[PDB]
Length: 370
Image (tube, rainbow, N blue to C red; front, side):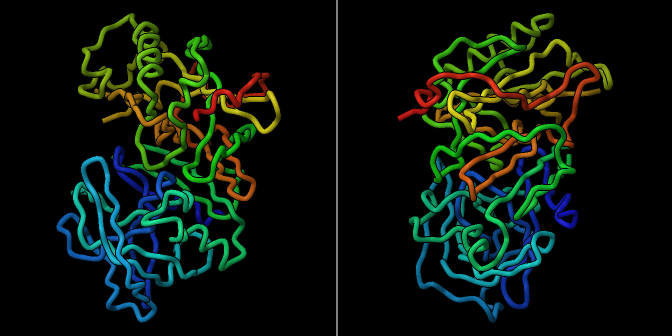
């Protein structure tokens, strides 16, 4: 597992990527690790923002599936040819498998000018793969063609260049401290989980647990910050702008519109409230909690910081902001996601992030949106 350590790189705000090789001879590409989608798609044409791209034509192992694919977004999209080829992860398990590849030949608002990645690795379930669930996701094809245990873990470390680790097939005790707690994967499409309670500085937000999972809650390494629904969002700010009211910030900051700055070395961390997310446990009426420090939701850019915790209207998304404080275990084999304080978390000299339990929480199911 140590060979897989520190196998993820990136730039704050634009996700983490892992090196991969496709085709014969192997072609090297940097791929975004996105637990929020399910397609393995790489640029396969000279788009100007690309450092390099997959060249099917030169892979003696490529196989055109004579089938195209279109993936639209709120404003952008990507399209390309389907096929398969021998895939591998240099700094991952010493294996090679034949996986489906989407050769992107046209896209818009997909690639990022400046970024060092050329493709995306959707690690979620087929249920949301495009064009349809028939397109077997990479991880699925991996576990099948090999003896790599059906699970992977992520240790996103943030900082500007960021780093992280993607342990495929197992757990590396060196990446976390303390206890590992598991929340169930409600449904195998997105990595869906259930938030049954939220606290700020140890104080409940006093809200029906259903409003936390409207219209769903997911774990996604492909999103930058914590994204709560409106009701949850406002409530979360109202309490935070009030928790650190010993100062003042424009209406822009609390929207990522603008930021705040303080002499290097002298940041008022102590005035900012920790956030507690209570996740459904493995046992009936049992839950546990994870708490995020200010560092997590105040992303750097003297010292200046932008407000991560942004609104949302597509359910709770536990992005990098969240995931960077913990070592997340995507135990696919047992339909569950585990959490544990990451060994690469930035802490205060006073406070500390945690993952504690068990807690008694009744009727957690009613928190699930339908």
